Length: 236
Length: 241
Ligand SMILES: C/C=C/CC/C=C\CC/C=C/CCCCCCC(=O)OC[C@H](COP(=O)(O)OCCN)OC(=O)CCCCCCC/C=C/C/C=C\CCC
Ligand SMILES: CC(C)CC[C@@H](O)[C@](C)(O)[C@H]1CC[C@@]2(O)C3=CC(=O)[C@@H]4C[C@@H](O)[C@@H](O)C[C@]4(C)[C@H]3CC[C@]12C
Image (cartoon, rainbow over the protein chains, first blue to last red):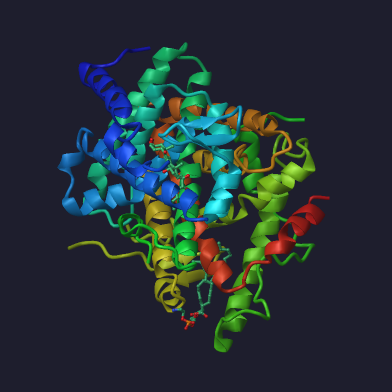
């Protein structure tokens, strides 16, 4: 029934900070892309907003303890695989159950119908189901921040110092254990919570492949997927 | 009725399937573009695959409370985990043939007692990476973890008992069955290996590595029209009676 070291809380603190630090893209960036007072419009916004999301996700990843201890080779490896899966945790946080839609950083609500129009009709029914499941999950910003971190040092194929990352991860994995162990009576349910959360990992893997298939079924429809995204997700 | 516990389960792993019904979830479709000199073997492989599926289809159903949940769901839960289950069993069996400036990639993948798959063959089938992922991320990494039968059949039940599967008439009816399992497992680690800082997580962290591999193995299966896609629910349904 222990508490947490100083590091831990400094990290949790730190992570909760960077998270709000990066939830949305800057007012200027946001302003620049959203400028404007035909199926390329929803498409432009969704794609353009995603490029901002990824960027934020990347910078957050570097503000992570232990990240700079990774080979540039691995860093681009971890980041490259996490880019799409964290972006998933982040669409959950801006989901609104009342309307069953996702809210973009410009305060606009995108429905399953908008994603249709933009030709993303494939990715939406599943993305929105994951949101309903993350909703009833009812998680706090610590979880989310910790979870994120974890996903990033999640074992990925192509890793040079695999064993290294595993521990860089064992830490965050461990911190989360503790924080859950305090937030409630270190009783039975304490694991049940730790488990459902770690379960998010596997679902996030399925939505990751769907994002890729969407990038594929989009290059194939000859539709310019931003080079930036095509590159980071290894979209052939 | 009995309590869903690691105990009852281990008494189900040993249970033998009833190869009475021939259900082809996997097969060489006439519309398959699999070379001709390999239709006999690839077909033969599918047939093995099939037994096992029906073998887990009848294990799933003999799980504490599983048969109670509404069948429609029951179908969907199975329909949604067989590949994963199928692959996990392979990784388990493969642990044996594990060879574990010193090490090279494993060369054997045990499909069923006795019979095995050699690396170079998967290499000829263009499934060498996925083959490699199965033996590294799963079999090897497990050996390392020294996971035992109690942990292994637990994970299994957990894999099958997924509430996130889309379309569940009553999600929470599954969440209970899962949450029970989350407990049974946590204590088992407590009781049987309390010296392990983070085992509970290391075991549950195989679940994603597994999901990805299974997700990939579907692409390959589909590129070859190997899966009886539209007809699986039925066999699942049909067989669940
Ligand atoms: C989840 C598993 C469920 C049930 C398990 C078993 C049933 C599924 C079938 C899996 C076959 C495993 C590969 C072994 C192939 C053996 C035949 C061989 O040597 O073919 C060479 C041929 C060269 O011609 P090719 O056309 O010229 O060249 C190939 C393309 N470069 O290759 C072919 O004919 C390719 C056949 C396609 C086989 C299906 C591949 C999907 C398997 C991935 C699933 C993971 C489990 C198995 C891991 C080994
Ligand atoms: C192929 C690729 C383009 C598809 C990605 C699509 O399927 C996703 C997952 O659906 C994309 C589309 C646009 C999207 O990038 C976003 C817009 C925002 O406004 C914000 C910007 C920033 O605050 C993020 O922290 C959250 C959010 C809501 C992201 C989340 C992921 C979204 C919702």
